[PDB]
Image: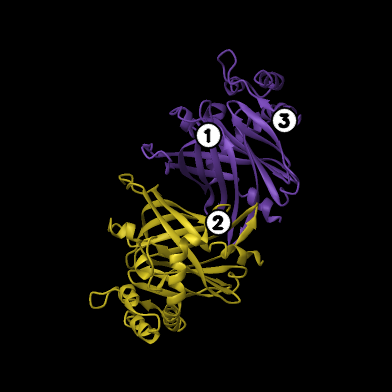
Chain colours: A yellow, B purple
Amino acid sequence: DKRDITAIKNMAGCYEVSFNFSETFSPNKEYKKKDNYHSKALEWVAVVEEQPNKIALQHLLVVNPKGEGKNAIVKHWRQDWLYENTDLYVFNKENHWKYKSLNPKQVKGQWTQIVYQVDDAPRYSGSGTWIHLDEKTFWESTADAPLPRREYTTRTDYNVLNRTNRHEITEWGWLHFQDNKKILRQDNQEDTIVAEEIGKEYYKKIDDKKCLIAQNYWKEYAPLWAAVREEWANKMNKKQDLYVKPKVQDTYLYSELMKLEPQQTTEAKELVKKYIVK
Amino acid sequence: DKRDITAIKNMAGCYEVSFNFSETFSPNKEYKKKDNYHSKALEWVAVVEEQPNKIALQHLLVVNPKGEGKNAIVKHWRQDWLYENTDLYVFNKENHWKYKSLNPKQVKGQWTQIVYQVDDAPRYSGSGTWIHLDEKTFWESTADAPLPRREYTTRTDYNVLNRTNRHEITEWGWLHFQDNKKILRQDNQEDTIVAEEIGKEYYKKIDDKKCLIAQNYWKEYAPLWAAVREEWANKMNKKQDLYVKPKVQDTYLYSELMKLEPQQTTEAKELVKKYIV
């Protein structure tokens, strides 16, 4: 179904995003639910790569609309879509992502979505079939993920967020629905659900012109980010587990990459390798 | 798909149900969320009617497992499944259900689930396709519905519950996931969503023995209820709107039927037609 490509590419554009999360259930009766979350943003999603069965989508955030360049844009998670892919990198705990090879017969008709981090490192991976039935266009998958900032800045109750993600194309844009389980993963033990949350992320399509600051940034700095991507790919094509340093020399990778200029491709690649433990 | 029929019939058996409801979002920022609802129950789901394009499932609750017969059993929502159905009764508001016709083109591959109440009156209807992909077996649809007991016993804040219902077959049984919206449809202001709720009902499969008390009741009282279904069907097959009197003589219908005996079929059909306007 080629309607599958239409749906992925319908997640591209200029959007005003409403971020919303509410806690729901817990296996502990004494659990005290945390207050609900709401944020807002201006996001431009771009199609960085279109290949025969690969579509890559980069999210960029416009923080200052009255500005120009990189100081007005903050990069956001990338979303890569691969058809009938058997090679996945999934989150275990901490800074460990493990290679998982899927059965090639279960991934038939399916698309794998690999969501990446701001520094372009792997964040989470899942596979599923796009459904174009009942006047609805949706995709669902479940994936273990690193804790987001809204959570690590607020609590230490858990280490893995299991996300059941749903991507639905809508009249006004798209919705990223999430039914998440907050899990405590400890070694040689079974996972424990500390709590659960529901999230509804609304992307309302607006005119592309209102996201021009980001389009102009990417025109210039795209070649650099392609090299960052290529290096991560070199590691992950070796099909071995990935361990990633969070900070080297009290500096994070995204910050170092951002300081770099558009043509400093070689330098960028060396930086990625400096944050890969192997 | 054949697997379609297999999926509906896997929603049957003896189950231990866990009911879980949590309010989530509201457009009123000053809204105070209500406490979460949790309950448990023992239920028997049975296949009462199976024809090629219609499968009906009756839910019966065992309230006392050390009991005998009728007073140990409480009737629960019937679930009728109809393939490629164009005739639906949809909840509007306040004891009124409106007839809706659908174009056969929209319902291809789809099944309609009409959920009925304890008095076998209609509650909600919706249509959707069963998905058998990704090692998952699911069905989803959206339907405006009347308020449940959990809510009418406690709130007058709203009058219609919009429900997005997901029925998924699982190894342990089935799950009823609910993404619902709480709406006030009114006068002097229009549809207001008061709050949103998420519900997850877990129907875990257990030994049939635990549900026999109910199986026995059904063997005896089945024909009375077949008769109640016959009268409602008469009204509904006339494809016109339905208004149901909530109470006559300050008496509810289920209560009257529940005061009857298997033999009393005519009286039942008569009691039903008393509450039909």
A36 versus A145 height, above or below: above
Q: How crowded is mark 3: few (under 14 residues within 10 Å), some or many (20 or more)?
A: some
Mark 3 secondary-structure assignment? helix
Same chain shared by disc 1 and disc 3: yes
Label disc, if present, on residue B191 of the rendered structure:
1
Circle 2 chain: A
Residue at the spot of label 2: A168
Instruction: Say if mark 1 contacts mark 3, CB within 8 Å.
Output: no
**In the image, what residue occupies the spot 51% across and 56% down?**
A206
Say if residue B9 shows up in the picture. no
**In the image, what residue occupies the spot 67% across and 29% down?**
B225
Measure the C-alpha gap from mark 2 to mark 3: 35 Å
Circle 1 chain: B
Residue at the spot of label 3: B236
Q: Nearer the viewer, mark 2 or mark 3?
A: 2
Q: Which of A38 and A154 is in front in this view?
A: A38
